Amino acid sequence: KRKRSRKESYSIYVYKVLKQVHPDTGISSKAMGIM
DNA sequence: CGTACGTGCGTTTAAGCGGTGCTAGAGCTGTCTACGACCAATTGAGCGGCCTCGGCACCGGGATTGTGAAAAAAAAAAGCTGCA
Ligand SMILES: [Ca+2]
Ligand SMILES: [Ca+2]
Ligand SMILES: [Ca+2]
Ligand SMILES: [Ca+2]
Ligand SMILES: [Ca+2]
Ligand SMILES: [Ca+2]
Ligand SMILES: [Ca+2]
Ligand SMILES: [K+]
């Protein structure tokens, strides 16, 4: 096992900016996909 | 059914032409060095996997607020005059 490739994405940085501008609001996986 | 737009005319304008004179700056060359690629070593930021726990989808009951449809009233219009 331990495949799923390792696919890079901006989602940690998106979350990081989100917590700056709106610290109590989160984000669905589709919405993250669009970001 | 009313007039905005196409046609044609006379009047006016300035584009185009060709020419001249001047130079800003496009673009090329040579020099030199600050910067970015390249490399190996190192390791923590970010990856996948995994579990949890509350957001959010779904439910039922009733009040309330849009959202419109019909029915009822009000009005404007149509036809009819009876005098002066
Ligand atoms: Ca005229
Ligand atoms: Ca120059
Ligand atoms: Ca870590
Ligand atoms: Ca994850
Ligand atoms: Ca309901
Ligand atoms: Ca309404
Ligand atoms: Ca309505
Ligand atoms: K340089």
Image (tube, coloured by chain):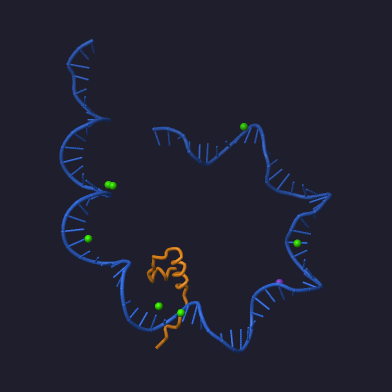
Chain colours: A orange, B blue
- The percent coordinates of residue B40 (x first, y second) are 61, 89
Q: Residue B77: give x, y in percent of width and height.
A: 26, 30
In the rendered image, which quarter is residue B36 located in?
bottom right
Q: Position of residue B4 (x, y in %)?
A: 48, 38
- Which residue is nearer to you in this view: B41 or B73? B41
Residue A22 visible at all: yes
Q: Residue at x 42, y 65 (%)?
A: A23
Q: How many marks?
A: 0
Residue under the image location 47 percent in, 67 percent down:
A17
Above or below for B72 versus B39:
above
Query: Which one is in front, B46 or A1?
Result: B46
Residue nearest the viewer, comparing B28 with B76: B28
From what the image shows, is residue B55 above or below residue B17? Answer: below
Quadrant location of the N terminus of chain A in the rendered image = bottom left
The quadrant of the rendering that contains the C terminus of chain A is bottom left
Q: Which residue is pictured at 40% across the width and 68% down the height? A: A31
Task: Give the answer, above or below, for where B52 lies relative to A31.
Answer: below
Q: Is residue B2 left or right of residue B17?
A: left
User: Is any part of residue A7 visible from this angle?
Assistant: no
Horizontally, is B46 left or right of A25 in the view? right
Residue B26's image quarter? bottom right
Q: Tell me which residue sits at (42%, 85%) in the image.
A: A3
Establish if A23 lies above or below B7.
Answer: below
Q: Quadrant of residue A27?
A: bottom left
Q: Is residue A9 left or right of residue B49?
A: right
